[PDB]
Image (cartoon, rainbow over all chains, first blue to last red; front, side, top):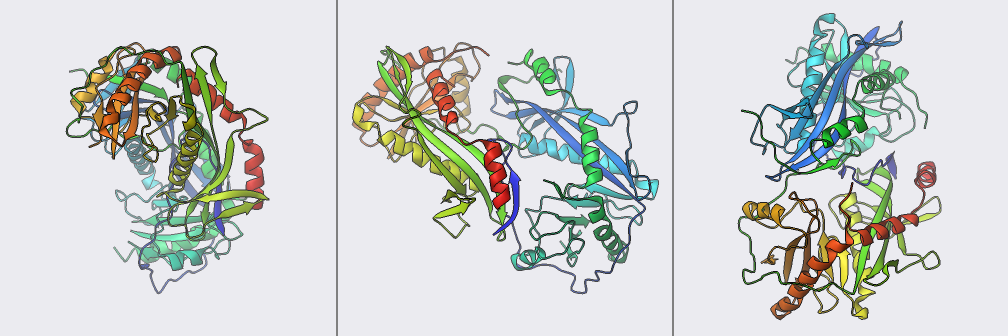
Length: 287
Length: 293
């Protein structure tokens, strides 16, 4: 019996693992899933990465030349969705060279006149790059904290940035491999009607929200963020997003990749360097 | 001072959803057969190469959370003849082995075959993840394709790792040819010496400890690790070592003549390209799979 299906893009694709569960689910027994409304405005923040060239050093270390582009849109119940950047004021774009933390050096690599920041906090090159784009993302959330508008940030919640009043930020999680719930409860989720939410659970607290119809974890998303007097504040935010987010999507052929977010991702991609151009430039100094 | 990054290999990255590539791995001490020495070899008159090609379609998640992958594997062989170069040991009228598989982790508890849209997929589930299960199955298909040619008294070279299921036999091998040399099986300082091997040169043989024997060979000119492959085989009697030594000498001599240094080795490239012909169109398969799932 099938809960999700996705097309495979290449023969080198991530060996994706089975979903992971826990022995017992840390629910909030008193889960008050009240009804919500519709938010006037949500700010969405996300990042796009482009990967150019993989190298191996003389010490055996694998490195990845990449570029990360991060930014934001405003959604508006009245006023659709718009970019917080423009060709005149382009979103942040950073060239990086990712290594595992086994790489002994630090700073910048100049290849072909272009400086690539060495980024090496992860266990391997690509994880180091993902860790870094997360920090740039956090930085972009920080650029609008005082706007008094709810900020939804693609990916995991940001430990660095705990939950505020009318802002968040709130992590939106599409890939739910590590479920945090147990199997008997997760299994249960698949029968959630388009718009319903689970009971909140905590490690840092989370809730799964369903965004379309038909059973199975497509449309299933998980909201999460990081003083227990804040729970009523954010519990409303969860009650308001489970209302609001289904209206910002639809189905066609993806689902969980919500409309404003796809518009944002399209827009960041516009700013990324052409792959063939960049690779040709880099290869003139590597090979 | 300015940052010194010494690059031994560089490769274009094809998509963003790739399995993470890790650093190369080393061992504390290299177990070289120090008595070994490369001697001049002879160009082989014939070699059979065996390889496989896979095409992945759709990834699924079951209700129990097990990630699954629908795929197809196609396996076959070419014979390379020093007079007549390369031919497929298969043809459109006698097509190579093609199997549709549904890969899962060990955690999958059913078995046999799954039908989807009237198409049978063999459940394949030996591994830790779905793709691992697929790779182990093609390896088993490649081993079967080797067995088919053992009778011919011709050297057989299998793309990928040596197969312990097939210990070295005197004229035939098989010999594994490893081109992805991440787990190096040598110490770092010894591994670093290899980038200086010249074309047609091999390291000394080295041993795993029922034993694997291996040597590195340099197939092209120039001093990085492109062109560096590992030949290896499993050996039963240590008195077979002389015979393996000669094969390694002969492959070290012969294989560089079957490469280009320009933009795999050529016979294998031709094999893979031909195998590819027989694989099912992706748009067709994926649409039918998504419809019936």
